[PDB]
Image 1 (cartoon, rainbow, N blue to C red):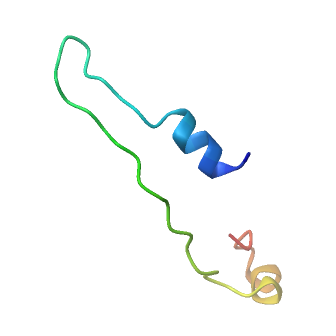
Image 2 (tube, rainbow, N blue to C red):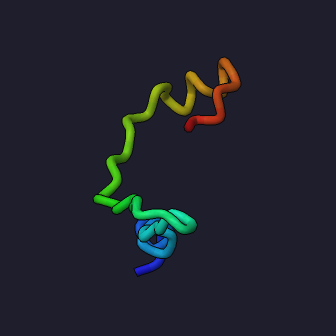
Length: 48
């Protein structure tokens, strides 16, 4: 269903313009929160 996953498989297959070279998409891996939300507020790191 919808999500970044849906967007990736939306743009997954790539064909080189007049070329034979492709970029297949395999499952993405989510990162771990670099900061805590309270720490982000203390610093301003957008809790990304």
